[PDB]
Image (cartoon, rainbow, N blue to C red; front, side):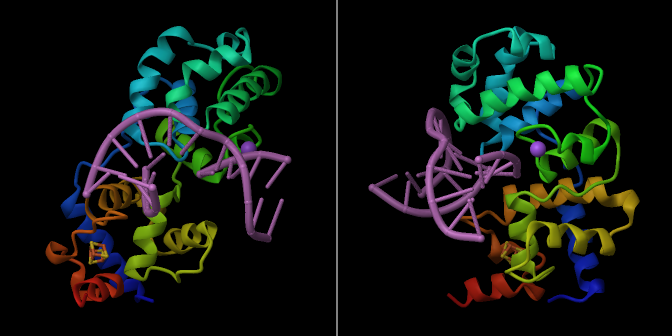
Amino acid sequence: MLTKQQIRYCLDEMAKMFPDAHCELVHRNPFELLIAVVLSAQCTDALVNKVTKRLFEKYRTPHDYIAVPLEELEQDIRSIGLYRNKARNIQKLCAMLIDKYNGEVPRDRDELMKLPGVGRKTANVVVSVAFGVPAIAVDTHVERVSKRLGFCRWDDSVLEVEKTLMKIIPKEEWSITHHRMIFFGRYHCKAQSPQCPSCPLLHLCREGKKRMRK
DNA sequence: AAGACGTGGAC
DNA sequence: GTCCAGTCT
Ligand code: SF4
Ligand code: NA
C-alpha cells in the first residue's frame, strides 16, 4: 500500500484535475437531497435527475409520499430500477420523519441510518452536502479508486476505506476530497475504461502499471 | 452471510 | 449480450 505522503500526493493531483468537483444530484433542500441520494444507490446521476425532475413537482413533503398507494409511487420512480424496494423504503422513511424526527430530515448521521433505505454512504452524503458536516461517503467510485491506487488493500471493507481516508485527510477537507475522488473515478479512473496512459498518477499506481503492461 | 433487487446506458 | 451506476433480509 502507498505511504501517507504518497496518498496525499494522489489526492492533491485529483484536486488539480477536478477543481470543480461537486455533488451532481439536483436538489433544492435537505428532504429532496435525501430522497435523491436514496434513489441514487446503484443508479446513474443522469437518470436520478431526469426522474426527480418530475418527482419533486408531484411530491414536496413526506406527507405527499405516504398519501399515495405504494403501486403509484413505484411507477413514478420505475425508471430508477430497484423501484419496488425503493418505493417501499421511501414511504416508510417519510412516515418515520413524521413520527420520530418532527417531520424534518435529522442532521445526525447515525439517526439518518435508522431510516429504511439509508445506509452509511447515504447518510454521509446527506450530512456532508446538506448540513456541511465533514464526512467521507464511500461508494463504488471511491472504493475502486482507493483500491486501484493502493490507498488500502483490495479486500478492505467500505468502512475500512472510510477510516483510512479520515486518518490521512484533515477533517476540514473531507467533503471536497470525497467529491474529487468521485469525479476522478467517474470521469478518469473509470470502471471499464480507465485513462491510465494519460494519468498523472500512473507513476505510482499498481493497477495502472499492470494495465499498461497489458 | 451470500443473494436479491432492476431499469437504463455504454460498448 | 455483458458490465457498471448500496441496502436489506
Ligand atoms: S493509472 Fe489508471 S488505474 Fe491508476 S489511478 Fe490512473 S487511471 Fe486509475
Ligand atoms: Na437504514
